[PDB]
Amino acid sequence: SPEFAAYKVTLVTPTGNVEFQCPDDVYILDAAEEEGIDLPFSCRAGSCSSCAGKLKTGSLNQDDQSFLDDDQIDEGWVLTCAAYPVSDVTIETHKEEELTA
Ligand code: FES
């Protein structure tokens, strides 16, 4: 494993695609906000639905999230405030309304 790495993050938002580099040790949401991007959030701690998105391409680490159950992780759900990229990723944002619980 490299000590450090950078990953291309593409966010498909309701109003456009936005893209940015994200370090291996920076959450999706923080890397987006570093580039002026407006995403939904609240707790910023991985324990709610505000920042939910759907993984479309690549792989994510979500050790730091606690709200999504294993079934939801297997459905492609992502808490963008608690997810690190481990590859180039594409994520559809603003998806909280699709969650059941
Ligand atoms: S804002 Fe609450 S889990 Fe991300």
Image (cartoon, grey):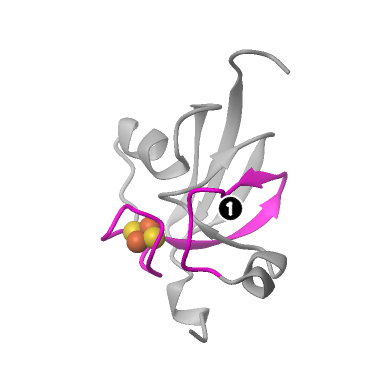
Query: Can you give x and y, in whole percent of width and height, for residue 43 in the image?
Result: 27, 59
Horizontal placement of 50 versus 12: left or right? left
Q: Residue at x 72, y 49 (%)?
A: 57
Q: Residue at x 56, y 37 (%)?
A: 9
Can the viewer see residue 9? yes
Residue farthest bottom in this picture:
100
Q: Nearer the viewer, residue 15 or 50?
A: 50
Q: Which residue type does callout 1 highlight?
A: Ile
**Vertical comparison of 51 with 60: above or below:** below
Determine if the magenta segment contains residue 79: no
Determine if the magenta segment contains residue 45: yes
Q: Is mark 1 within 8 Å of ligand 1?
A: no
Classified by dominant secondary structure, the portion drawn in magenta counts as: loop
Image quarter hosting the N terminus:
top right
Q: Residues within 10 Å of mark 1 (few under 14, many from 20)?
A: many
Q: Nearer the viewer, residue 93 or 59?
A: 59
Q: Residue at x 66, y 69 (%)?
A: 70
**Vertical comparison of 1 with 82: above or below:** above
Query: Can you give x and y, in whole percent of width and height, for residue 38 in the image?
Result: 30, 49
Magenta span of residues: 41-68
Can the viewer see residue 40? no
Ligand 1: image quarter: bottom left
Query: Can you give x and y, in whole percent of width and height, for residue 27 in the image?
Result: 45, 39
Q: What residue sits right under mark 1 in the picture?
A: 91
Q: Nearer the viewer, residue 72 or 54?
A: 72
Query: Can you give x and y, in whole percent of width and height, for residue 50 in the image?
Result: 36, 67
